[PDB]
Amino acid sequence: PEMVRQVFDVGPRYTNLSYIGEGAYGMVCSAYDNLNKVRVAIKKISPFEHQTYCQRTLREIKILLRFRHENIIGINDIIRAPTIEQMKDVYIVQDLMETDLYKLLKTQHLSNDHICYFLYQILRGLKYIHSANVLHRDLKPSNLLLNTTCDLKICDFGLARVADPDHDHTGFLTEYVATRWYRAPEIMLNSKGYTKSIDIWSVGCILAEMLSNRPIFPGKHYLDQLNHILGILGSPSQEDLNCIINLKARNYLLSLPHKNKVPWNRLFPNADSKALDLLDKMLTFNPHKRIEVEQALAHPYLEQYYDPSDEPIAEAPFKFDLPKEKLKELIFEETARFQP
Ligand SMILES: [N-]=[N+]=NC[C@H]1O[C@@H](n2c(Br)nc3c(N)ncnc32)[C@H](O)[C@@H]1O
Image (cartoon, rainbow, N blue to C red):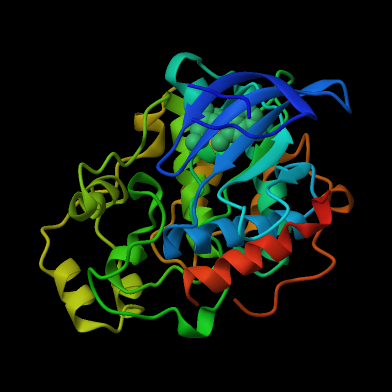
């Protein structure tokens, strides 16, 4: 098998490999697709030793194979051994994307037109995801891929879940949903992250980050995150507190000194006022008052792009959400369509 930086066993269809990046149990390379005569991205995944890894791998594969949308990364092919016994790794082949929003924001200032276009594409993809009754649950710049013409595709559904609002409530300081900086305040207070509003919060954080090239709520650790959120939004209203029945959560908030809201236009003096209005509606403390994806698409900031007839929804929503060996068998089965 061809080697990179580690076995990268993808031939003969895919050749001329170039290292792109790595992970805890995989590696990403670019490669030439000899059938389609174009270069592609290939992700090597080696999840079989660990149950949790098998879970995330199965979620990613099952969701992406079922979704078909311009703003969601597709799976073009899956490479693996012909038998379960011989299967040690799985390679997911995808469209080759020039960069991601994390990398881009490290060195590039976005024009207002780019911010608007990117946000439109994120929400368009998210509308489809939510219409399938699915929560992405880890939206952040590194999970937004971009090609050389700024087409944006949402990736990494390994942490996704089927929405379950009737079972969202939980206690204080227990939950661990999303990546820290993109995590909604309620995750720390009383939410398991089983409602669509969790994703809208993350999009708001991404919007803020596009406006300034710095994360808006840069918590230094899990417990610090709420400090940053409240430091900008200010103290929640009585009405918003009244919505939190859990006493540990409500009393924590009541114990804090009063904090004033910091106006968005002071944080972002160069920003389009319509962007800031939308930002405020996504970064609303009360998840019940928080703007929903279809409302966000219809906001004046996005008027140049908005067209509900060209913002498709899923044909077939997911209706509902085991040892690593069953999981391996399921991954083997889910990937069979691509054999030989
Ligand atoms: N592990 N992982 N490696 C992370 C690197 O792979 C990059 N990457 C991913 Br994930 N998918 C990609 C794709 N379809 N095309 C190009 N680069 C990609 C990503 O931007 C990051 O740089």
